[PDB]
Amino acid sequence: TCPFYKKIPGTGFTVDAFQYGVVEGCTAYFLTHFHSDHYAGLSKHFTFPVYCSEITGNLLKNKLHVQEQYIHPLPLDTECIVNGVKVVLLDANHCPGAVMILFYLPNGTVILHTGDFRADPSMERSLLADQKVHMLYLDTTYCSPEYTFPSQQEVIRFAINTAFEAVTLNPHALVVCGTYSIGKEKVFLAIADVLGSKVGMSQEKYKTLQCLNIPEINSLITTDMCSSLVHLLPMMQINFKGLQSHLKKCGGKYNQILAFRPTGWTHSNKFTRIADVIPQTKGNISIYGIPYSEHSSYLEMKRFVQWLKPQKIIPTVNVGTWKSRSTMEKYFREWKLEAGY
Ligand code: NI
């Protein structure tokens, strides 16, 4: 049974609600982004209208085989009427094709559903500037002040400088980057660009990337692993055992691995600056965990909510414990008392 925080009142709509069977009253199912916790339950046998971005709809058609007649792609930043209700999709600054959804209810209520997002001051000049929001369905993944991490640009600067140094010292080093979903593509694309290489990967991963409308992608990626000095591997293989095994397969072309694991936040963020990050090393293998987030930090979240001034907040993450819920509610009230709304 579908939980309340996935339903949009006053409509026939649900958000990210595909794992509950046929939801009573639902005439259109919205999908914010192509991450498995959110698409859980979609497959080629789905027969109700799915509304989403163009990129999400490429992934549904080619990776999940959803039939074309049930996929309804909407342009961004454009007022659209769906089953008699005005909606807008906005870029969520999450993974490729991820959106926030603005719903203009027939009674005058305005609802923003963030999906998953990384709040940014650029959102203060989208179509959100123009009107009041009554209800905010909020991605609360990192809603506590201990959750700090650097900008994506500082993280990428670290990665490119680390990779370029290592490979200039040893031209026979291979770089490997872990992946298990879409998102975070700038990590491996920025490192390959500084090294003058295409990125090499499995046919399954190449297929996924080919759905993402990235400019000039054919110039940036390949399935010919032998021609590439930046490889992608599943995240589960980014360990000393799995990397040893990979280095054997490369036919003595390489004699060292430098590997990256983009994580979200880890507790080493509560002590160490990005500049001071060091790898774990065993012989000719080194592994860097880098804090590349596609979710809001606490400060970024707070800034966004204090600017938007919603009347009511409904969290969509960390909802399963009373301690989490109470924590989140306390910070919402602080934010409102501090800013005066
Ligand atoms: Ni996500």
Image: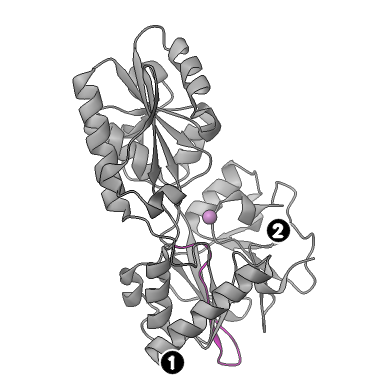
**Residue 116, magenta (yes or no):** yes
Element at badge 2?
loop
Write the start and end of the magenta stretch as one range: 104-117
The residue sitting at the front extreme is 271
Q: In which quadrant of the rendered view does residue 130 lie?
A: bottom left
| Between 219 and 101, the one nearer to me in the picture | 101
Quarter of the rendering occupied by the N terminus: bottom right
Please report the residue visible at 26 percent of the width from the left and 34 percent of the height from the top: 162
Q: Earlier in the sequence, mark 1 or mark 2?
A: 2
| Between 230 and 80, the one nearer to me in the picture | 230
Residue 247 is left or right of residue 258, and the answer is right
Residue 96, percent from left and from top: 44, 52
Give the foreground label among 1 and 2: 1
Q: Amino acid at mark 1?
A: Tyr
Please report the residue visible at 74 percent of the width from the left and 56 percent of the height from the top: 19
Q: How many callouts does the rendering have?
A: 2
Measured along the vertical axis of the image, is residue 77 above or below residue 155?
below
Residue 70 is left or right of residue 179, and the answer is right
Residue 179, percent from left and from top: 48, 37
Q: Amino acid at mark 2?
A: Phe
Residue that numbered label 2 is attached to: 18
Please report the residue visible at 67 percent of the width from the left and 68 percent of the height from the top: 28
Measured along the vertical axis of the image, is residue 20 above or below residue 292?
below
Element at badge 1?
loop
**Residue 35, magenta (yes or no):** no
Residue 104 is left or right of residue 174, and the answer is right
Q: CA distance from mark 1 to mark 2?
A: 36 Å
